[PDB]
Amino acid sequence: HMEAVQNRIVEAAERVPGVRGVIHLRARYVGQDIWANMIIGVDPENTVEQAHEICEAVQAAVCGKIRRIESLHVSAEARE
Amino acid sequence: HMEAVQNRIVEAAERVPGVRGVIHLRARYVGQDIWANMIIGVDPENTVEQAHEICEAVQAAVCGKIRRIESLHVSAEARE
């Protein structure tokens, strides 16, 4: 029953400047810890550097709000 | 192990305009649901009506962010 935690991850991610939706989220329990992988949408006209910064901001925001997450990998794809 | 959920309640409550800290929070599981009772601080110079509105706003904010809560009673006390 991972809906509640995944809902929290998505909402946290979406509240970060530059996030155009969560394209993909795979979360799994490793013991009582969550390890996750996420792909966010970003403006196709952002620079690669900006997209990297937005990914780092999502990582901080999400990990800050969901204490059980012990690994979170965030990548980005162009989204209009 | 109610720390994580109680931390979430407190943080949610504090982010509501007019909340001057959480003075008291008693939360308990009833099955897999949380029932809670909270006292917030408010400006002593707010009206009784305003304090009521702030309590209602905390109730909405908290219940909106913590899905397992099925009852939340919020009251207010003067805090400088």
Image (spheres, coloured by chain):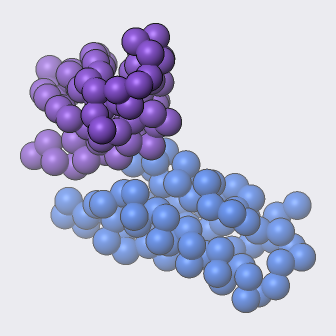
Chain colours: A blue, B purple
Which residue is farthest left?
A: B1
Q: Is residue A5 left or right of residue A48?
A: left
**Percent x, y for residue B28?**
13, 27
Which residue is farthest top?
A: B49
Which residue is farthest front?
A: B45
**Percent x, y for residue B13?**
37, 37
Q: Is residue B25 positioned above or below A12 on the image?
A: above
Q: How many labels sit on residues?
A: 0
Q: Which quadrant of the view contains residue A75?
A: bottom right
Q: Is residue A56 positioned above or below A14 on the image?
A: below
Closer to us: B13 or B20: B20
Closer to us: B71 or B54: B54
**Percent x, y for residue A64?**
39, 64
Quarter that holds the C terminus of chain B: top left
Q: Is residue B47 left or right of residue A30?
A: right
Q: Residue at x 41, y 19 (%)?
A: B51
Q: Residue at x 74, y 59 (%)?
A: A20
Q: Is residue A55 left or right of residue A46?
A: left
Q: Which quadrant of the view contains residue A17?
A: bottom right
Query: Is residue B33 among what the camera can see?
Result: no
**Percent x, y for residue A27?**
42, 60
Q: Residue at x 71, y 79 (%)?
A: A51
Q: Residue at x 65, y 74 (%)?
A: A54
Q: Is residue B69 left or right of residue B53?
A: left
